[PDB]
Amino acid sequence: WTTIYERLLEIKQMNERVTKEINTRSTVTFAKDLDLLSSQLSEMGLDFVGEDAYKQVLRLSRRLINGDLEHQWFEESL
DNA sequence: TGTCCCCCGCGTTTTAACCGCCAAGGGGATTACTCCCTAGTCTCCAGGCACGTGTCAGATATATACATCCTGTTCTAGAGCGGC
């Protein structure tokens, strides 16, 4: 329990920085023109944009325990 | 018959083998729609089969000729003996 608690503390302490990192993810428009952005997790909804990172990680852990997340995709998302 | 070197029995230390556990994602298995081509005939005709036959390559034949193998004779090297 203390190990899981400290892991989630490590998640939450930098959460206020990563949340504004993905919220202000300034995608360059030139790569938008000829389609080089990584849209692998954007197709099935594993992206973190427009939403708090900790709550999304909580739902991700819930579905990861549920066994319908295709583990390596959750690995790449993290 | 001998030998010696090639293989077996055993001590030690790694080493990957098997089972313990977890996902992954191509992939075997199943179901369904549909579409091509293969089952089944009609007719025929042109390639395939039975018959007939001139013929041209193979076999028989034999003196001739290969052709290699066996054997006899001679050449040369090696060991033994005798003299200086």
Image (spheres, rainbow, N blue to C red):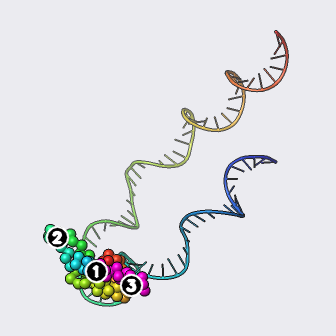
What's the mark number on residue A6?
none
Q: Image check: A2 left or right of A77?
A: right
Instruction: Look at label 1 and name its amino acid.
Output: Asn
Chain containing mark 3:
A
Q: Nearer the viewer, residue B42 or A31?
A: A31
Q: What residue did someone put label 3 on?
A: A5
Instruction: Look at label 3 and name its amino acid.
Output: Tyr
For disc 2, the neighbor class at 10 Å (few under 14, some 14 to 19, many from 20) is few
Q: What residue did someone put label 2 on?
A: A28
Q: Nearer the viewer, residue A31 or B3?
A: A31
Measuring from the top left, give residue B79's x and y in whole percent. 78, 26
**Residue drawn at 21 percent across, 82 percent down:** A50
Q: Which span is picked out in magenta?
A: A1-15
Image quarter of the C terminus of chain A: bottom left
- A28 versus A15 height, above or below: above
Secondary element at tag 2:
loop
Measuring from the top left, give residue A43's x and y in whole percent. 24, 80
Q: Nearer the viewer, residue B17 or A25?
A: A25
Alpha carbon of mark 1 to alpha carbon of mark 2: how far? 24 Å
CB under 8 Å between discs 1 and 3: no
Residue A48 picture quarter: bottom left
Mark in front: 1 vs 2: 1
What's the mark number on residue A15?
1
Chain containing mark 2:
A
**Residue drawn at 37 percent across, 88 percent down:** A66
CB under 8 Å between discs 3 and 2: no
